[PDB]
Image (cartoon, rainbow over all chains, first blue to last red; front, side, top):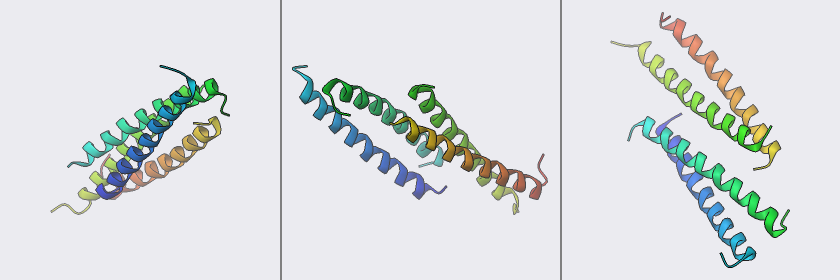
Length: 34
Length: 34
Length: 34
Length: 34
């Protein structure tokens, strides 16, 4: 478990988290006025 | 840039990831997406 | 069980794993100390 | 997060956990520690 490996993991999770935020936005656009 | 700072960032982002996973799963049931 | 309980167990095991990796790094240092 | 997906994750982290626990017990002896 090197620093590099942990840095890659943080980058990977941030990207996934961003996709999830985009999904919440997409789904919120289908539901209503908010 | 300690290993501990990186591990804490992973834990922080993973918890954030799951909270978003729960939100998207909920919005999906609302819109009719399965 | 719920998704929440399973998400809690995942976060718990990852934290325990990171600590075990910290121990491995600490003990590897001790084997050849001079 | 699907339930099966989370269950598979716990199983994956548990296996790595025991594999780590085994490695630290080996080093502990190699270093004369407790």
